[PDB]
Length: 225
Image (cartoon, rainbow, N blue to C red; front, side, top):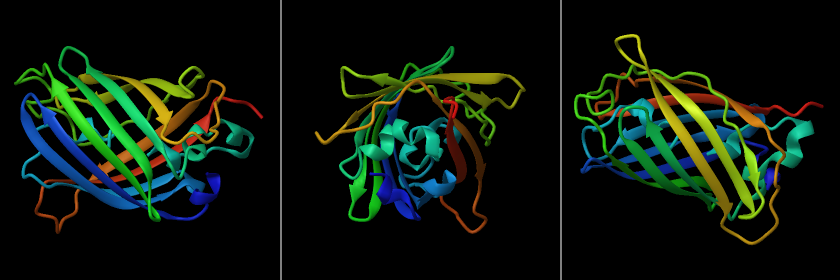
C-alpha cells in the first residue's frame, strides 16, 4: 500500500463522458508525488472540442496521491487499497443546473496508477454556466470531508466545489462520493478527517488540441497529533 507511493509514480487518466448527449473523451498523463501531495498532469480532449468547461472535470479526472501526515497514516484508505485499487463513485450536483454521475476504477496497471472513468451528465441548461462555457479557467482550494463507510468496507466524502463565473458569481458543485476497495484484502477505515486541496489550471503554448495543464497539492488534516 503506502510503499507504492514513496517515490514519483506515473499516472494515466482515461474518461469517457456524455453530457446532455454530447459525447467526448479525455486522456491525461503525468505523475504523482504523494510524499509532497503533488500532482502534475496534462489532459487532452481526444474527440475534438470539450463540450463542458475543463474546471468542471478536475475532481473527476487519484486521492491516493494525497499527503497523509505521519500521525494520520492509519487513516489513509486510498493507499491501503493499492495495488488492487478502489472504485470511486460520485454524484456532482451543479446548483441550478445539471448533474454529473461518475464511476471510476483507480488501480495500478504495471507500475502506472490508472484512473479510468465513465461520466454521465444530464439536465444541464444550455446557456447555463456549464454548457454556455461561462466558468473561469481556474480553480479554488477546498476541504474534502471523509467519513468511514464501515458497512461497505470503504469511505464516503462530501464537499462543495466553488467554480468562479466570468460575471463574478460563483457556481457551486455539490459532491457526494463513495469509495469501495476492489480487492478483499484489508484496508484502513479512517476516523473523520478532511483533505485540504489546491490547484491551478494553465495552457501549454505549443498544444493545439483542446487541453488542460493541471498542478495540484493535497494534504490530509483534521486529526490532531
